Image (spheres, rainbow, N blue to C red):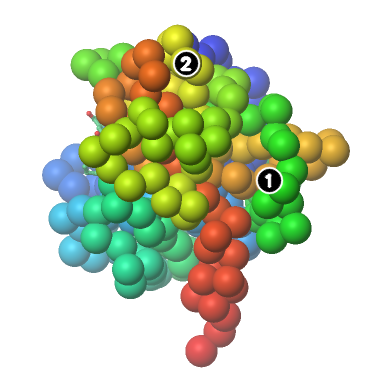
């Protein structure tokens, strides 16, 4: 996160850090608890990942320093990537992780509500992007979970800023015209969380952008409301 500040412990209890153990253990991506056995994240996080056996999901983490060999984690039983996904910049950048065991909810770890199709008209003015990513395009993973308040922009405005791309209605953008605050490398897969009427909703999934926090280059997020039917379909038992 560029231009952000340290989070308070427990203030983003749906935020997880997804690790890979290969070749040695490191943070791979953010993600969001959306159900007792389900993390919502970005499809691009699994580039080159051949098996869910190398993944570990840590919840209730503020500092990466909390994670040691003796720290408990959730195994991943299944990675579910949208079947239309090709790459982050052309959309469908959404994935579900089915955990091997269930999360026991507490104030350190609990789910975020998915948006309602009826909330498509709501004007959110209290949106935050969070993660352990770079503070600048050339940087490194941060110890403490960072947060930044960023305004949503219209898809028409976002499209003007990305003329070589197609910004679809299945994407949503956020950023300041002057730049300065944004997601960056290592933040992808995490939430864009918007508070409205005292309730948090998972509005976006951190997906891509041109550089980090640049002037007139909004962050691009997966527009989660467009995938509520997909999420229901994929999280249904078989
Ligand atoms: N406004 C935005 C939003 C997202 C942006 C992204 C997202 N990509 C990303 O966040 C990419 C995604 C990725 C995942 C797996 C394989 C390849 C790429 N992630 C990373 O580049 C990434 C992830 C985990 C890491 N852990 C480490 O220990 C050290 C790293 O250097 C490291 C880098 C990148 C650049 C600008 C952005 N601007």
Task: Residue at 33% x, 21% y: name it.
Answer: 212
In the rendered view, would you say 169 is above or below 237?
Answer: above
Alpha carbon separation for disc pair 2 and 1: 24 Å
Q: For marks 2 and 1, give the one nearer the viewer.
A: 2
Residue 204 location, x and y as percent?
53, 44
Is residue 210 left or right of 38 when viewed as pictured?
left
The residue wearing badge 2 is 177
As rendered, which of 139 and 85 lies closer to the eye? 85
Residue 146 visible in this rendered orientation of the protein: no
- Give the label on residue 181, or none: none
- Residue 202 is situated, as x and y percent measured from the top left of the image, at 61, 46
Ligand 1 shows up in which quadrant of the image? Answer: top left
Residue at numbered disc 1: 201
Q: Is residue 39 left or right of residue 142?
A: right
Q: From this viewpoint, is residue 139 visible?
A: yes
Q: Where is residue 112 in the image (x, y as percent from the top left)?
A: 66, 48
Task: State the residue in front, 89 or 157.
Answer: 157
Q: Residue furthest right?
A: 197
- Foreground: 26 or 210? 210
Mark 2, Cα crowd under 10 Å, few <14 / some 14-19 / many 20+, is some
Identified at 70% across, 28% down, the residue is 125
Quarter in which the N terminus is drawn: top left
Residue at figure coordinates x 34%, y 38% from the top left:
208
Spot occupied by residue 49 in the image (x, y as percentages of width and height): 21, 57
Secondary structure beneath dot 2 equals: loop
Note whether 79 is above or below 62 in the view shown: below
Residue at the spot x=44%, y=22% of the render? 182
Report if the beta carbon of the residue with label 2 is closer than 8 angstroms to ligand 1. no
Nearest the viewer among 168 and 53 is 168
Tally the marks: 2
> Which quadrant of the view contains residue 139?
top left
Earlier in the chain: of badge 2 and badge 1, it is: 2
């Amino acid at each position: 996160i560029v231009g952000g500040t340290a989070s308070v412990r427990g203030e983003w209890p749906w935020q997880v850090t997804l690790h890979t153990t290969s070749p040695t253990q490191r943070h791979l991506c953010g993600g969001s608890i959306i159900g007792n056995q389900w993390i919502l994240t970005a499809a691009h996080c699994f580039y080159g990942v051949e098996s869910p056996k190398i993944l570990r999901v840590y919840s209730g983490i503020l500092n990466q320093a909390e994670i040691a060999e003796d720290t408990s984690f959730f195994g991943v039983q299944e990675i579910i990537i949208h079947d239309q996904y090709k790459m982050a910049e052309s959309g469908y950048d959404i994935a579900l992780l089915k955990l091997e065991t269930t999360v026991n909810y507490a104030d350190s770890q609990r789910p975020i509500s998915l948006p309602s199709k009826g909330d498509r008209n709501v004007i959110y003015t209290d949106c935050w992007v969070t993660g352990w990513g770079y503070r600048k395009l050339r940087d490194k993973i941060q110890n403490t979970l960072q947060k930044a308040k960023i305004p949503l922009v219209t898809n028409e405005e976002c499209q003007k800023r990305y003329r070589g791309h197609k910004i679809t209605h299945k994407m949503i953008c956020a950023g300041y015209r002057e730049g300065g605050k944004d997601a960056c490398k290592g933040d992808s897969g995490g939430p864009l969380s918007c508070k409205h009427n005292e309730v948090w909703h998972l509005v976006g999934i951190t997906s891509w952008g041109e550089g980090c926090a640049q002037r007139e280059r909004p962050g691009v997020y997966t527009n989660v409301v467009e995938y509520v039917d997909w999420i229901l379909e994929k999280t249904q038992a078989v």
